[PDB]
Amino acid sequence: ENLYFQHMKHGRVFIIKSYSEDDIHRSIKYNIWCSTEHGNKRLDAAYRSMNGKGPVYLLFSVNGSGHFCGVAEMKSAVDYNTCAGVWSQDKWKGRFDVRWIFVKDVPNSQLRHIRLENNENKPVTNSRDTQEVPLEKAKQVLKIIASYK
Image 1 (cartoon, one colour):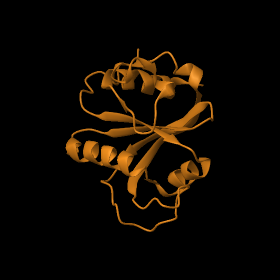
Image 2 (tube, rainbow, N blue to C red; image 1 turned 180 degrees about the vertical axis):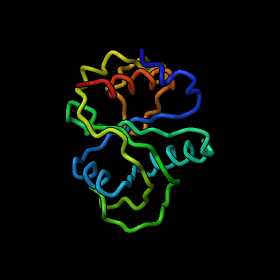
Image 3 (cartoon, rainbow, N blue to C red; image 1 turned 90 degrees about the vertical axis):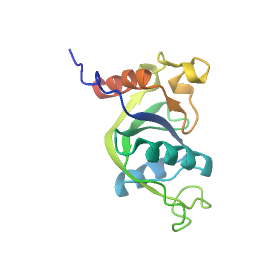
Image 4 (tube, rainbow, N blue to C red; image 1 turned 60 degrees about the horizontal axis):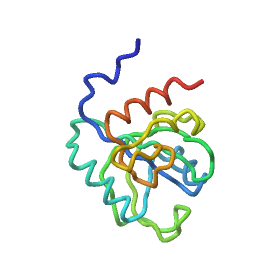
């Protein structure tokens, strides 16, 4: 029995879909991330709305990699005016702090059977960047990622 995520009634979870393995590596090295402008605003609102009352988790996956590659917690609001050209999209300016939790590869086949009711019942593995996960589905995804060997 692992009932750790029971009573966790606060927290929000988003899918991060990256085109670049280099961005993932930079993120792990420096504990930062940046999304599109749309994605950043979505993450920033969730972070600011949380008021430190619980975590904002990010479930990372490189497009076409066939797997998720880990989990980080969002650790600051978005700073929208930072040095350009640090990411795979050279136009991106903007940055927020993250803290990586799991760095491990989890095949999509381990997660494909969990579906998102806010995204037309599609598999969580078919999500787009900054797709939000309902908390009840996010608990199941996290337990799977933590347990995978």
